[PDB]
Length: 122
Length: 121
Image 1 (tube, rainbow over the protein chains, first blue to last red):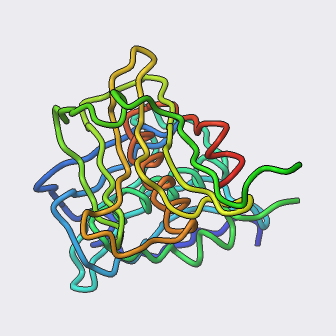
Image 2: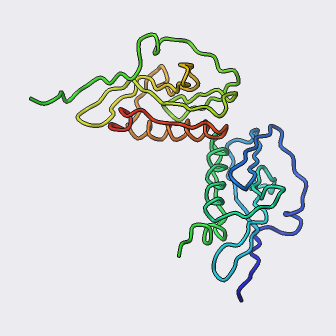
Image 3: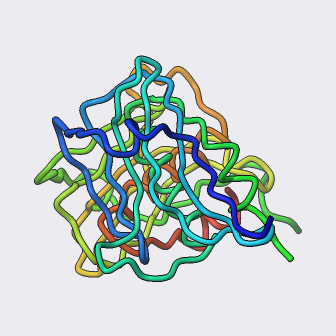
């Protein structure tokens, strides 16, 4: 099947409202990165929702960052203009958020489903 | 013939080492034996990391002070051993520097490492 939607998150998790106590935000190419500076010493799970064409990444719809208690503390997503992006853009945006969260000695686990596609080649 | 097994590498001047600097908006971390700091206000600049450090044979042994400088000569960042001085490794420094670079890059600063730090890191 040549188009699949890979959904780390639930519906409720995709659309939930969240807020940063101490906002940090950055534009990496065609992607916006967000993280709450207030958060420290937490293990953090990256959950991604994205699409895939044949066996390669198509689009990242949304990635959110979760504490082990289910609280959202960060997010990556496409710029409101919704432009095209590469796996490399993504690899890069994920790296930059890992660095950001790691400042307050949080541990970050990437989405294994996304990384399986984003760290691919030809 | 050859150069000592111990050398002292000085990318900075005495005035450069002892100068105080202000972080407009502080961003500090401790990585074990190392303090990392930088000014969060700083944006879109070109920045060079410079270092005063010891070498044994061909590898950084002990860091004395690393600073981050704007093209104008303003210090915008710093990696310094904590003052009880409980020992760090060449590797502990490579790592700290990655953390300063990434933190600085957040605000679209462009960062270079000195050629010295490049040889002996």
